[PDB]
Image 1 (cartoon, protein in one colour):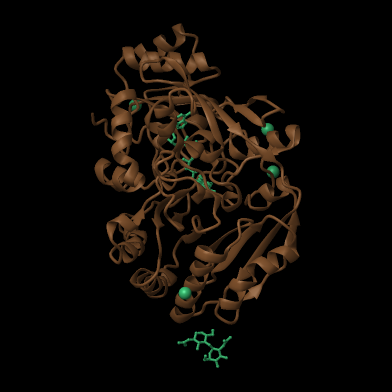
Image 2 (cartoon, rainbow, N blue to C red):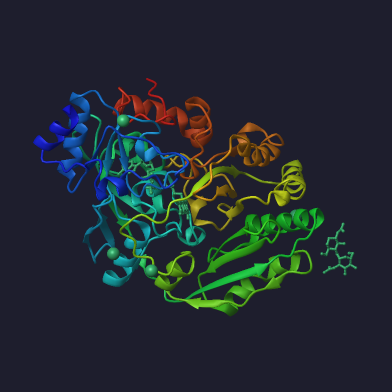
Length: 473
Ligand SMILES: *Cc1cc2c(nc3c(=O)[nH]c(=O)nc-3n2C[C@H](O)[C@H](O)[C@H](O)COP(=O)(O)OP(=O)(O)OC[C@H]2O[C@@H](n3cnc4c(N)ncnc43)[C@H](O)[C@@H]2O)c(*)c1C
Ligand SMILES: *[C@@H]1O[C@H](CO)[C@@H](O[C@@H]2O[C@H](CO)[C@@H](O)[C@H](O)[C@H]2NC(C)=O)[C@H](O)[C@H]1NC(C)=O
Ligand SMILES: [K+]
Ligand SMILES: [Zn+2]
Ligand SMILES: [Zn+2]
Ligand SMILES: [Zn+2]
């Protein structure tokens, strides 16, 4: 067909329907949302990426990059059938490392586990990114990237010092603080909007030698306990929590909430740093035993797998997810949250679900040392990052009536807050919002600048997906 012929003439490898490569590359991480691209360009070089974009232009197609394919909305496909899909996951190398500056150049199909493995094993270096080893560098870094080092060292995006980008017109350009700084600003938080990143240029830190994983089983058996407890954790997060502590409250057992965390220091140093919160928690919590880790052991520890060096996709899932970023959860917000928690959520027994309340902001959070004005990322004024997750078996159909579960929980918080108090996080992409509403909540106070930037770098909407920023001049 026209697109196949076009790709072939340009020397761009293409997946053939019916082959193993096609079957692998076309599989969404969220099998709730499969999409059928018109063709899959399995790129090996920056030139292939540029050729693919060129082919999209001449055949008037929409083009979408897929890196680790972890988009909760399958946006790597385009969020709909019929795009040219630029499949990036064979481009996995740390192109170069500079031992004078600590800057690594990295290909856009490297997964977080593979990246961490190469930087640590080969160079003794580390970056602050997410926990899941199969996640793509590109989708992740482009929109933020939060994990168990973000309090200490900031977002994955905060490591970005430069990018090589393929634009909607197929030109290759460099972006950094001193070259195309407007484009650089957009890539660092809304990067799916402005081109396909071909090379990430990343600042690293020495791989930590002394880390302690900690956990506390909270044992909140009623509404009172959970209200008092979430309050105690916010206060600590807002005012006390030292730089070295990274943690969240999570519940993976429909009523068995815990704190899990990573501390930059010894077990004794953690205990002293956390003790003020321990003194305010409702009585009946149990401090679980600590685990002493080095950098690469910690990556493995929070993995949920027996290895981390992933160069292929991780097992697919079948789910819906939502998110919230909040200034505070105090007042009616936490009251409504806890009611719903016990009256509704804890009686949902037919599938696996979770929430995570991430300590994202607060006084000593590195995330918060960058303003909303400095990069595309719009949540620098938010203490909490919240994930809600609703997962069925792969052989089951996600039922239409099941959406209202996470919808209800999110509403219970939002109805209690002014609109300026909360947003949503595009790395926990929720496709059940129209283009205008979603970009309002994903990008906050930065949306007006993003729209103007979009009208400069993608006026035709070549990179269209249902939740892309609108080009507005
Ligand atoms: C599946 C999964 C996701 C997780 C997990 N844990 C996370 C955590 O510890 N911290 C977080 O902050 N987020 C976590 N997430 C969510 C993921 O971070 C997001 O789902 C990321 O967006 C995933 O990125 P990726 O795997 O690369 O997703 P894609 O579906 O390929 O792309 C998403 C988005 O990005 C665009 N895009 C891809 N590639 C490029 C390039 N090269 N240039 C520009 N834009 C690109 C896509 O088109 C799409 O729009 C844990 C788990 C298990
Ligand atoms: C919620 O649960 C907690 C403990 O799980 C309750 O506190 C316990 O119950 C009574 C009343 O305070 C005390 O005699 C116990 O010793 C408490 N146990 C612990 C471990 O502290 C609390 O009362 C409950 N709140 C309610 C039911 O409203
Ligand atoms: K198609
Ligand atoms: Zn590897
Ligand atoms: Zn308080
Ligand atoms: Zn293994």
